[PDB]
Image: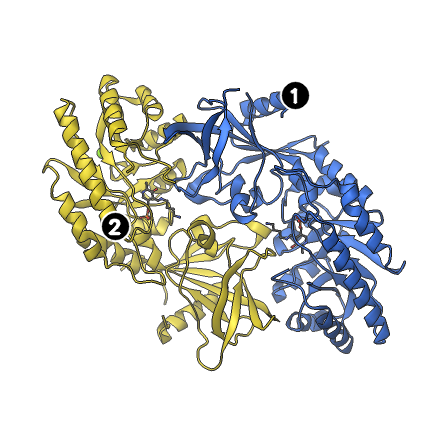
Chain colours: A yellow, B blue
Amino acid sequence: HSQSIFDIHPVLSAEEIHLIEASVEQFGAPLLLLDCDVIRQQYRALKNALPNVTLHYALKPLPHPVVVRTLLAEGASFDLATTGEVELVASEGVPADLTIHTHPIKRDADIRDALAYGCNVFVVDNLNELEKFKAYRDDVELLVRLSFSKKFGCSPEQALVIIETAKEWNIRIKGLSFHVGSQTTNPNKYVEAIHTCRHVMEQVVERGLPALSTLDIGGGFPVNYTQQVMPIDQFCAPINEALSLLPETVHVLAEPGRFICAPAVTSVASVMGQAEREGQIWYYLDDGIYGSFSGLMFDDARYPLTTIKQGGELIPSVLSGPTCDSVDVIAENILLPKLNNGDLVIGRTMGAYTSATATDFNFFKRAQTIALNEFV
Amino acid sequence: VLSAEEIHLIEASVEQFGAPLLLLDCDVIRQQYRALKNALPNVTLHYALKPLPHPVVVRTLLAEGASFDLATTGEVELVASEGVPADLTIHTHPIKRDADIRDALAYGCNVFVVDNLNELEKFKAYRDDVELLVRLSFSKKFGCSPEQALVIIETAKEWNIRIKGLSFHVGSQTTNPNKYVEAIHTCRHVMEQVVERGLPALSTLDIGGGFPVNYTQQVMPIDQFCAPINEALSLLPETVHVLAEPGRFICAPAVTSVASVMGQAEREGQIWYYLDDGIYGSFSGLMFDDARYPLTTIKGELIPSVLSGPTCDSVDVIAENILLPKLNNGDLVIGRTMGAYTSATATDFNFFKRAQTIALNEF
Ligand SMILES: *[C@@H](NCCCCN)c1c(COP(=O)(O)O)cnc(C)c1O
Ligand SMILES: *[C@@H](NCCCCN)c1c(COP(=O)(O)O)cnc(C)c1O
Ligand SMILES: [Mg+2]
């Protein structure tokens, strides 16, 4: 569902419109336009906002080989959750030492597959999981994931029990991790977590256990959809302050996903047909909630939407997806100029938890991703 | 409950193929088809591929004498690849690109649906080749008003486009057959108005899908469900041929899901089990189909538990509160009535493998 252009030969600009129209002319709709310049911009902005933190890109929101290559070249590390993600980074020549595996609940095979690639950092949040590493004790170092509806992470008290048990079992503990949740708009969540982890690290030392080397602050850095979020520097300011209280012997990781990929993709769908229903014009698009807009369902999402056509009468409209399902609706009420069949509907901030969560329902073709600007 | 033989079959399948699995019983496909045929005498049944577009289901139904209801080029390619003659098919997507029409025609499917004049116009170029069903609604996304149906039928005559008849779809998992009856009465009246306007008489009524199945609560037996429907159809002229587009009724009961426990943890007074299938996989119907499936274990000291899917996402939970016996890693969680709008709406999120479908009793 993807190809690259390596040789090109609120309101959209004339240049953007031209690119969009040329792309539909060349490749046909629906499309996802991936701009590698934005991947780099986002990575650089986060690096500048969170100095002295190793950024492990979480493949989950957009596990795209071009994104992986772009980030590798930029100096990024990676956060893997499955054998499939291990295989993707392996195929793109990512050195295993740049990777961590963070799925807290793993089958024996999942551990073996990652180890075979060379990824040797894993996460545990319970004793049942810890036991799985006895057979691998020479080979691994573990992050213990804390939580403070949450599905993963143990309590601070449980974390100490896990760490003490790992010592008994001769299993190395690399450090602690947490994930405050995706699209977190309040940085105080990070601050409170960091303080708690710091206190846990102190308790480990006071108990005479090996001192922890690493804090992994997870993902969740927010981006703008239809509402303004805190600028990344301002967002990370209190985070940086909390981190500064850690011992100098602790180094810090994060697992950003959405922040890096979300702004980098623009969706393009076309109108297949249309009908007036109870005073609204319904447009039936070639992409929807079983496709690139699946984030409306799984990610509680809302994306800015626009049209190339602008000006004249704005009409109460409905944007429907292509499937036969009445649930497949992208915008229940939206003002739009009158569109003809074949006219384009554009979605912004379409990079994260979109195509990643697409289906093949009805066998409608998935949007094709077009990768731009990888080199230079 | 699971029978001793069901348990043996499930365990044997996991022994051979691993987990997660979807066990597809072709005998149940046959049974459901035969039961609906008996319940709705003289109605031609077009299986909707959408809920479960599996090659073995298509072959099984073809052999049974079934017809087919297609929505997309992909579905056209599926029945074609399984050798289904085009005359057993109808294409029912109301909103089509020119290519969608051409692809269906290439295969030989010549029956299409329209619910508006914009769509009707797409068929001028194919007037020699097509006959159309006009879809009424009485709900939200498709179907014109009875008054609009008349405008469409009249301008089709003007444009020299053939109208096969009328269609409707009252909605999936319709538990009250009285919605069909009201639909049928309204269509009967539209048919009368066509004749009274001096237009060509309509040959066909398509009553759509929506026949319900038992999930966690029982629904009315199919014979009883359809009794009032047959009564309503009996008031039609004897010359009208009746079609239906059952999906869920045929496929839903034919599949049993099998997942295994990858790991587990106590989280505030509940044991969480993390399965190898979930809301991004076979249980995607929890999201898209507003579904709830009966869930059981192979195994009496029922303890408060949560069933989570495999993905990292906190949304990926199958059951928030369920009483289960204590399970060990590797133990199985079994879902019933897992045939329809399940695997069909699976994703590849996190690159977790989709459950493998195992066809049983194919021959
Ligand atoms: C992502 N977790 C699931 C997000 C599901 C969205 N519908 C996750 C990330 C990346 O989160 P992000 O908000 O920066 O994209 C990082 N680390 C862990 C452990 C995650 O689960
Ligand atoms: C199915 N329509 C969408 C169902 C989405 C469920 N989440 C459909 C059918 C088959 O319906 P069923 O209830 O018998 O499976 C038949 N005909 C049409 C036109 C449909 O859209
Ligand atoms: Mg290392």
Using the image, determine if residue A310 lies above or below residue B284.
below
| Residue that lies at the very extreme toward the right in this rendered image | B238
Residue A3 placement: quadrant: bottom left
Q: Is residue A35 at all visible to an observer of this figure?
A: no
Q: Is residue A170 above or below residue A31?
A: above
Residue A219 placement, left or right of B77: left
Q: Quadrant of the N terminus of chain B?
A: top right
Note whether A256 is above or below A30 in the view shown. Answer: above
Q: Chain of mark 2?
A: A
Q: Amino acid at mark 2?
A: Ala
Give percent across and percent down for residue B109.
73, 58
Q: Quadrant of the C terminus of chain B?
A: top right
Badge 2 density bin: few <14, some 14–19, many ≥20, Cα 10 Å? few
| Label 1 sits on residue | B5
Residue at left offset 77%, top offset 51%: B88
Which residue is painted at 67% across and 64% down in the image?
A: B143
Q: As drawn, which residue projects farthest toward the left?
A: A248
Q: Are marks 1 and 2 on the same chain?
A: no
Q: Position of residue B335 (x, y in %)?
A: 57, 33
Q: Nearer the viewer, residue A259 or B40?
A: B40
Residue indicated by mark 2? A73
Residue B274: where, in percent of width, then height?
Answer: 43, 32
Residue A310: % across, % down: 44, 77
Q: Chain of mark 1?
A: B
Local packing at callout 1 (Cα closer than 10 Å; few below 14, some 14-19, many 20+) is few
A110 vs A129, nearest the viewer: A129
